[PDB]
Image: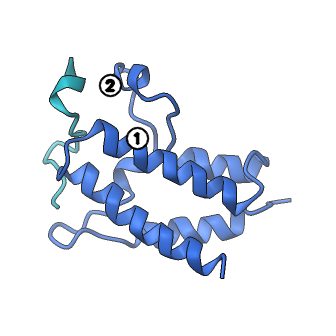
Chain colours: A cyan, B blue
Amino acid sequence: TARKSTGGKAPRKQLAY
Amino acid sequence: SLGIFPTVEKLVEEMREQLDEVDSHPRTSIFEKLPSKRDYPDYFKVIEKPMAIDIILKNCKNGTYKTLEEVRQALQTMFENARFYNEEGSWVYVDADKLNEFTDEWFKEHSS
């Protein structure tokens, strides 16, 4: 699947805390 | 001596040639180096053993990994870290799974 436009990771939401 | 570096460098080049079908990004891109501790400090508190392609290559050159078995486990850890940290179906998660399927085939051939 296409890369996120900024190149960032895709953490699960709970791990973004 | 270079130990197993020549063989693992070949594996890494083959991995880098696995490109996404839509945007052609190499599936290795996000695994080349560890996440920045500045950008993702909490990654280092949830992932017990960080691993990336640069570390695997350096470990082969410095003798820390002397066997393909060791590299196999390092890659397994790297992919497990990505499947734990990133949303299922995200670009990072899919790249981990596609690369893991590729490396599994390569290790099978090198264990035949």
Q: In the rendered view of the protein, which quadrant contains the C terminus of chain B? A: bottom right
Residue underneath mark 2 = B40
Question: Label 1 vs label 2: CA separation?
Answer: 14 Å
Number of residues whose C-alpha sits closer than 10 Å to that of mark 2, classed few (under 14), some (14–19) or many (20 or more):
few
The type of residue carrying mark 1 is: Asn
The type of residue carrying mark 2 is: Tyr
Q: Kindly tell me whether residue B32 is visible in this rendering.
A: no
Q: Position of residue B7 (x, y in %)?
A: 67, 70
Taking depth in this image into account, of A14 and B59 the one nearest to the observer is A14
| Residue at figure coordinates x 64%, y 77% from the top left | B110
- Can you say whether B40 is above or below B28 in the image? above
Residue underneath mark 1 = B81
| Residue at figure coordinates x 52%, y 53% from the top left | B75
Q: As drawn, is B49 to the left or to the right of B67?
A: left
Q: Secondary structure at mark 1?
A: helix
Q: Kindly tell me whether residue B74 is visible in this rendering.
A: yes
Q: Position of residue B14 (x, y in %)?
A: 48, 73
Q: Position of residue B48 (x, y in %)?
A: 49, 28
| Residue at figure coordinates x 51%, y 41% from the top left | B51
- Can you say whether B27 is above or below B47 in the image? below
